Image (cartoon, grey):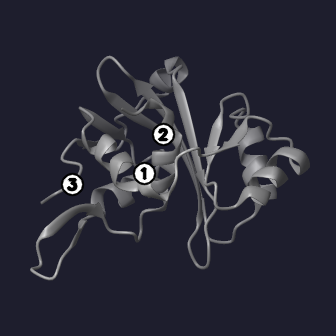
Amino acid sequence: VVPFENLQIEEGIITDAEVARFDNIRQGLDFGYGPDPLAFVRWHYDKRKNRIYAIDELVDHKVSLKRTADFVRKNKYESARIIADSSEPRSIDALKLEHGINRIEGAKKGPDSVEHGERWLDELDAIVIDPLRTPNIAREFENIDYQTDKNGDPIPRLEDKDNHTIDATRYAFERDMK
């Protein structure tokens, strides 16, 4: 009925000292399309505790690959891999060959992996988000609901709306699932 009961959301819940230690980084990127924003996410993965921690994000409705690469470079996030929305193969090429983001690769998983990937996220012990650091991730994860059928009952598919950072997060963790 309610997804992501596992959410741990509170201002200040991730300290500067913690961000300093996190060293199992996962990054995802959705390019946006039509009015939908580009959404870059960076997380830390504690595999033993089955937790993920949101570190940073960039959400931009006025999509600029230049601005995205500048943000990634500025924060020295270039050294960790970015798994990106594979529907824009030339945007990936652009970030690599034009903007020097070398560790970007297309998401290997296809459109039929969506429900699986969302379920994987929902089955984590905790998804830990500090709205002071990642306000968009916080808002989207808190407010996302299940889709529903004729009979008006929830199906195990999240709404495909206001979910741009959730998509980016799926890509970021695609290699960690099963």
Residue 10 visible, this angle: no
- In which quadrant is the N terminus drawn? bottom left
Q: Position of residue 23 (x, y in %)?
A: 54, 19
Of the two numbered discs 2 and 1 on the same chain, state the one appearing first in sequence.
1
- Separation of marks 2 and 1 at Cα, in angstroms: 9 Å
Q: Say which mark, if any, is on residue 29.
A: none
Of badges 1 and 3, nearer the viewer stands 1
- Nearer to us of marks 2 and 1 is 1
Residue beneath disc 2:
174
Quick one: 68 or 11, which is closer to the camera?
A: 68
The answer to whether 165 is drawn above or below residue 169 in the figure is below
Question: Which residue is pictured at 61% across the width and 78% down the height?
Answer: 34
Q: Nearer the viewer, mark 3 or mark 2?
A: 2
> Is the C-beta separation of discs 2 and 1 under 8 Å?
yes
Q: Amino acid under label 3?
A: Pro
Quadrant for residue 6, please give it: top left
Secondary element under disc 1, as helix, strand or loop, is helix
**Residue 110 appears in view:** yes
State the residue lying farthest toward the bottom: 150
**What kind of element bears circle 3?**
loop
Closer to the N terminus: mark 1 or mark 3? 3
Q: Which residue is mark 1?
A: 113
Mark 1 Cα-neighbour bin, 10 Å: few <14, some 14–19, many ≥20: few
Q: Which mark is residue 3?
A: 3
Which residue is more in the foreground, 77 or 82?
82
Question: In the image, 71: left or right of 31?
Answer: right
Query: Tag 1: residue type?
Result: Ser
